Amino acid sequence: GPGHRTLASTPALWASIPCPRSELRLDLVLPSGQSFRWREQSPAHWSGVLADQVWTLTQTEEQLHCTVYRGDKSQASRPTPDELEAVRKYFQLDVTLAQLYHHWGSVDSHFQEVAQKFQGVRLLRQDPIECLFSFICSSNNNIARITGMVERLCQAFGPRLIQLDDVTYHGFPSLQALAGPEVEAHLRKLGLGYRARYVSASARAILEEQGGLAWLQQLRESSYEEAHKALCILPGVGTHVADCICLMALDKPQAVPVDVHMWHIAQRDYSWHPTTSQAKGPSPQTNKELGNFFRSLWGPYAGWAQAVLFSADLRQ
DNA sequence: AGCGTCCA
DNA sequence: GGTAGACCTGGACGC
DNA sequence: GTCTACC
Ligand SMILES: [Mg+2]
Image (cartoon, rainbow, N blue to C red):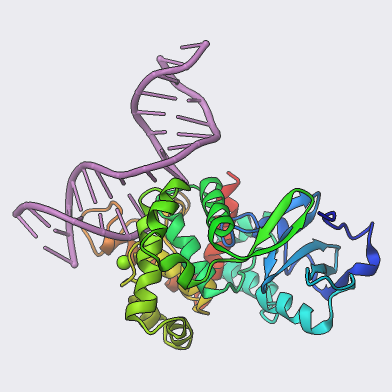
């Protein structure tokens, strides 16, 4: 289909949001394992699905430039202010990252050193359903493979949106699409491994046992502790996946995911060891202590600080 | 050379 | 609870 | 990273 746009080539189709590079680096956020659905289809231009539509995003020094492909057989035009609000909300631009970076660096000199090189790593505010099933796919897995699993899952079960060049975009599947008793076998053919059952069983649990889609809004409005505990009822969701969802979709900035990276970071970069367990290796008790350690260190937005160090550790 | 272990 | 080990997949890469 | 089984 039509080409992926670049800002310099189609300026009439773009609009900007005030956004200095100190507040956001697309290249350090979009491919770093928060969302798995963005691709750099042209140099410095990132395309993906945002609020049921395909967008391309690119940055200049002080502005985030956006273009939207509506795909309702309407004439091409720049994004409207209402449409740009969805982009603003997705990047949570109301939160000033420079002041968080100064706070985290002031309490943690290691953070300060890493942060000098990794500016503008902020937290996306993701759709709860997309975030839930993407991080169910993420456990005991690598970001390259996760990215393919999420792509194939959307191609098979999500609505077709539009085609740009040779790339066909799909929306994220609904709960209902993932809940059928045939879905697990299909997801296994798509290479999801043992997480195929987790995806289908979790879609069924939400629909059949938790009151449907409104449950995620309930958890958004609940405390961190309540939301984190509730998510763990889902097959494939343990304390880490629940923290990922809390932090990245349920507005819990203190949630600190603890994966292989953060465990290695704690040991290597902080010389940390658990003090509430004589055995020091990863365990339910020591993983929970490590999350508390990072909250005690970094404060109420510790999960956002985690995202800076996680993004940096992917490139080392 | 490419199997087979390591690892995310 | 605490502990141990199995587990789908496929790129990295030692031997 | 989460699940299951055993202590
Ligand atoms: Mg669970």
